[PDB]
Image (cartoon, coloured by chain):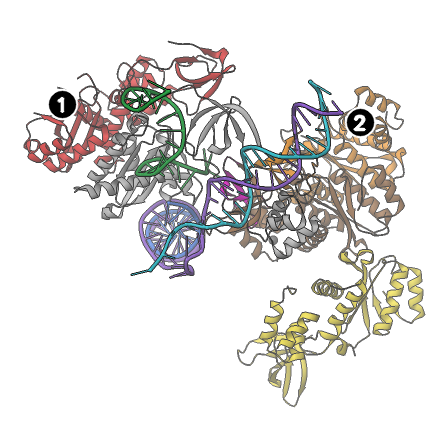
Chain colours: A orange, B brown, D red, E yellow, F cyan, G purple, H blue, I green
Amino acid sequence: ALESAQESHALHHQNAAALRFQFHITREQAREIVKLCPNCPRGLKPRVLWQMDVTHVSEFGKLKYVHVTVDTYSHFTFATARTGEATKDVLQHLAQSFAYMGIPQKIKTDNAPAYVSRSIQEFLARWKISHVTAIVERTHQNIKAQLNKLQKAGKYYTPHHLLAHALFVLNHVNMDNQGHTAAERHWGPMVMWKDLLTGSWKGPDVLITAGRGYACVFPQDAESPIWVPDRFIRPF
Amino acid sequence: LESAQESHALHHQNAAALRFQFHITREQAREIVKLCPNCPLKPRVLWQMDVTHVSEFGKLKYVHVTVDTYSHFTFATARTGEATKDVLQHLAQSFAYMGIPQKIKTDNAPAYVSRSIQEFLARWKISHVQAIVERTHQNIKAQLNKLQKYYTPHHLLAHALFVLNHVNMDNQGHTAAERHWGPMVMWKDLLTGSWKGPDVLITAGRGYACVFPQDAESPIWVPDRFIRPFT
Amino acid sequence: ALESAQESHALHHQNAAALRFQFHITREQAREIVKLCPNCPDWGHAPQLGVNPRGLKPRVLWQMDVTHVSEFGKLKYVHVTVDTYSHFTFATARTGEATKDVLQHLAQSFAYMGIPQKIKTDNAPAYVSRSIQEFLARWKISHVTGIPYNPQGQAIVERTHQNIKAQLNKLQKAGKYYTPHHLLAHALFVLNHVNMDNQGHTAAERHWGPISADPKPMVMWKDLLTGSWKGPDVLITAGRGYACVFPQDAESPIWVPDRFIRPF
Amino acid sequence: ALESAQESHALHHQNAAALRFQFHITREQAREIVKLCPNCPGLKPRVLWQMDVTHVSEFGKLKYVHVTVDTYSHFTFATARTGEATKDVLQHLAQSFAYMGIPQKIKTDNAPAYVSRSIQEFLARWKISHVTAIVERTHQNIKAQLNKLQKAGKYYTPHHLLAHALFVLNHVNMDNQGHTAAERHWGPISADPKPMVMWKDLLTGSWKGPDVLITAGRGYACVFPQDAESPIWVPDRFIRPFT
Amino acid sequence: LESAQESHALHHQNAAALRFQFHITREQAREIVKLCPNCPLKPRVLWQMDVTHVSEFGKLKYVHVTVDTYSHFTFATARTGEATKDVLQHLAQSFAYMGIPQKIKTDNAPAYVSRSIQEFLARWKISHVQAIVERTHQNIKAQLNKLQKYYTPHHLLAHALFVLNHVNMDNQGHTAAERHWPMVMWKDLLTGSWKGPDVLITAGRGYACVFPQDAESPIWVPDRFIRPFT
DNA sequence: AATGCCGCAGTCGGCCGACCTG
DNA sequence: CAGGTCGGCCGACTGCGGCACTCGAGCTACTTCCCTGTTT
DNA sequence: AAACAGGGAAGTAG
DNA sequence: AATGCCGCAGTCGGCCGACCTG
Ligand SMILES: [Zn+2]
């Protein structure tokens, strides 16, 4: 339990709450995990209002242009690094952002010429999206903090790999105080049964439904559930 | 049935997306898609990861696909090759896109079973080991063909990913993303009296069950007297 | 051993007892082996499941359907409306059936019985047409539809059709009647004030009068939605095919067939 | 609440007592509700009846209306008929028996159709004695109800209108004591065998009742509100006995 | 008739090849091909070769394909991968199978543009520097799926190659093998509406013979109603 | 100048051995 | 430990229905939709 | 030129 | 858009006042 958390943060550098919820540990245990770690020292509903801006990362070199797309509601963070910040670059990042997240309606940007350019406006209007002119810079701080943690973890061949790892650890596996990862917030009965083919009481495993005296017990068989008469089931 | 024409012209999604996002007739959506010229468990358990070649991208012909075996959520990238380096990069981005599963059922390519990938997968607590992956291949190729003027292969590839995931949905109305972040029964018809199936069971209770055949559009209510537990 | 049984069944589709006696396996194993084969036909002779609900208070839940009394000539379309708690019945003989005819029959039945909380019918076009819907809305009466092509959903009024037809045949054989309206009036009079049950209560004494509450028993109860025997619970009513338990935590009474009720 | 009372009075136009007893409105309030309406100005049941034939011009061809009133409960049944002859009177008698039941004896006037041998022998078959100011009152009441229901001229035939009027007069109109005509006619009138208990609804937090009880046990009681549809389980802390 | 049935059951050739081999009606060929459940300048000038994956070959999913642009003569050998040694072996075996070219067309994969392969091709006086190869890939995959029980992947691949090469013939009745070893504007004289373009078979002294790809038989038209194309 | 039957599946229950504990 | 207990086992029982010589056609009735004569 | 109003067909259920 | 039913008639079985009888 403890050593699993140690290895997890050592090669992954998670925060405290997510690790605690994953391994069911003491709060202190996670606190000294954070301390002893050397590398690790708005709308009303999802997909309504978005914020995006560019920022410069020193160690990315030719990929210093970091485009960040954060949903103002759930703070689901997505980011990519490209060679520039021109209209073509912003269009490419918007394409991959729509790929990553979905269809937004409200987008808030800065006064950059590329953002107020005609090509981006007509592209958004074609996709039925409205473009109008704290969150973005605090998200940038979080992203670059994750980066600063992650260099010494191991080898990272290209900045794209490092950026993907950082955004993953910041969205899909990290969570809030309420045990809720930003990723799922963007979209937010165990039984004992008798395998009466072999007569062995295999389990426990989840139940799905019931009826007709038949319980839809679903073992780890990724193919299909199986039906068992309720005379051959016992609650756990 | 007004915006559906331009929506299809932009994305080229299936008729189910039209009928569920625009509240139009099923036959109307079928006519729209036919007339178009360019249109001729639990999540995160088991994964399939294969490489495929597409000649459109040129030297970026090495497309890596990673489709979840439950929700059919699809991710892909185009890279200069298919070596261990490249599959490692694509695997990192796929994890960033879909989270951490526990089993990735892959083929027997030498780069896939090499050392570096092996300890990398060991560190992150993953196991190892088909029609789903080739079906996903066919869907990706069809979508890429249907997308014909984009900037770079990454652009239209991401667009294809987006339309495949967040736009299309099955008969139930649940998209790939919704299935990824959100029952099998034999039933008897009442008109002919002959059994048909097997079909999915939405919900049931107190003598009447709801059945949603994949070939139909609307749910069917049947009395519990005519329900059989397939498999 | 078991896999040999599976392949032998897949080849021949033997009987369950045949597999049991030939391969020395547990009987339930043979039953499951014969169950899992897609080729073997699925069970059609299913025992009784489900039950038609019925309001525990008079004038709560009605049922309605039409029939065909061919002896009436042009007035063969008979509308029948029967309560579910007391089996109080009413009927008229309207030429054809439509929105106007159903509305007139509904008004007559309302005058004859009273305001019902809700009405359950079949899915005939007249009962599905909007006009009836806003009529009931103005009269503050909920409406239900029922599963298409399922007469068991209106089994109560179907049995009432049987009773009415038998009574009409009896009366027609008895003597001479002026018009089908007179004959129907006499038949409804008999069925609603004379055809007493075996508990000293006519139809009127049940539909009206006081609801009787003797100390009701408590029984074990199989909840079909969880595959478990949970109880005990209060039993409200019972009969030849229905039972109405009412657990404290349950928001509403639950209707289950008799065989799922075990005394405790 | 009271707006629903006004809507119901608009639909049916029953007496004020019915509104004040069915919707818990103030008596005077229901009084002005009735006022604001544009067109609003024996010892045992099934024993003694009275029958007469009246005329109403609005029906035109069905002006022959038969009225059959019980003398204890005023339970009224009526029908619009094409003639006052013996056969129509017999049809109305059969339908009235279907509506109300078997009366011990019927008191009527000296109409020639009534005295006819066919009616006498028909009553002889059904064992109902025949003998030659309650129904002329009923003629006023039915006529008044027809006038008030003429607001919504969507009635297909006089049968529809008469059915609506009889429905109101027999199941909706309540006496000054709080009883409809049908309850008096079917006469369950006696001491209540079962207690009628107070009840405290959770949604309103008030003591609403009294309501009839079904069962009880293990800290809960199975109360069954009059207007409701299904029994409601209630904690005993919110249950008060009532006489 | 029945011989055609068994031939299509074994080899699963096209309708045209069956018709030309067994002398049946074109309608019969269409019916028989639809009925089967398993059915849903000069040679050696320029070549195209691109590798593709076939999942059901396991360790040998890296199948190479070489198609001549003239006669659509195809060749394939499933191998370990698409590295330098495998592509060199496949190229040598293709040379043995098909004959010496002058030019080869490939994509810009590192293996193809590798120094060793370029040096070897220069050693053979062959130069080196896009829908036919993909159509060939689709045909090969269709045949591989259609041919289903065989023993080894090489056996099944060889059988499918034989079916696609020495059995299937085009509308003209010429085998891909025999083909391996002009456009005209023609007037449909019946309707009077121009059609084309199509291949000219023979022409001279006022009359010509034109064989459109959609017709079962040659069409003879006079010289007055023939015009060139491109 | 001849009469409803019964397999399929669910289910109640008694027997009996492995197993608990007086 | 062996008397006491529970689960595996299945004997016995039973609710259900359709086998009967084959299958239809058609009516009433309301809604939604397309087509077309009439409008400004 | 676009709008609007009958009618027939069609789907559907008793 | 939300679930079989029950009367005609047979019949077992118990209650009980009457009748035989130890
Ligand atoms: Zn399209």
Disc 1 packing (10 Å; few <14; some 14–19; many ≥20): few
Query: According to the image, label 1 marks what residue?
Result: D136
Q: Report whether A132 appears left or right of A92.
A: left
Q: Toward the viewer: B16 or B198?
A: B198
Q: Which residue is drawn at 52% across and 46% down?
A: B24
Q: Report whether A70 appears left or right of B120.
A: left
Query: According to the image, label 2 marks what residue?
Result: A15
Mark 2 residue type: Asn
Disc 2 packing (10 Å; few <14; some 14–19; many ≥20): many
Determine the image quadrant of residue D214: top left
Q: Is mark 2 within 8 Å of ligand 1?
A: no
Q: Are marks 1 and 2 on the same chain?
A: no
Q: Which chain carries label 1?
A: D
Above or below, E14 against A197 in this view is below
Element type at mark 1: helix
Q: Which residue is drawn at 79% across and 46% down?
A: B129
How far across and how far down the image is residue A114, in percent? 73, 40
Residue B214 among magenta residues? yes
Can residue E145 be seen at all in this image of the molecule? Answer: yes
Q: Distance between the residues labelled 1 and 2?
A: 91 Å
Mark 1 or 2, which is nearer the eye? Answer: 1
Q: Which residue is drawn at 55% across and 45% down?
A: B212
For the record, the magenta segment spans: B205-231
